[PDB]
Length: 57
Length: 57
Image 1 (tube, rainbow over the protein chains, first blue to last red):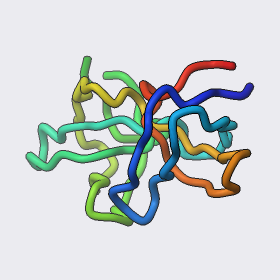
Image 2: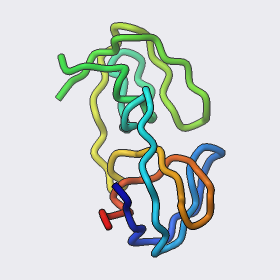
Image 3: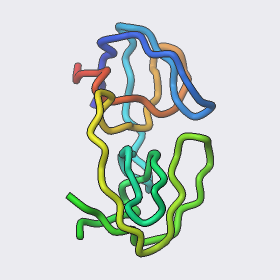
Image 4: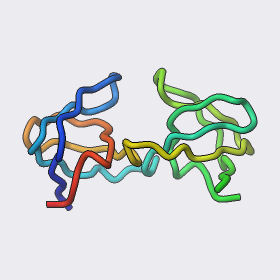
């Protein structure tokens, strides 16, 4: 239920969370699901997607 | 290996990927792992984290 940071992370956007090695973090369950880095074969664009919006082919 | 979008998604940041219902998307494996929404019990802050940076307590 609780995770521990193994490394320091500095936020790169307004939406990520900065944290330091050793911090205790809990996961927030939400409707979007885990986010994945994805490439659209249809548009050519690439970026993160909410995994509850997609399904395997 | 290939996923299909079930819904339309509009990007909210410079890092997410917009796509339309029906688009075919492939997952990009990378060092960060899936991203999770997380709450730091230590700082109080909340946002997305790269899951390869943490481990269960």
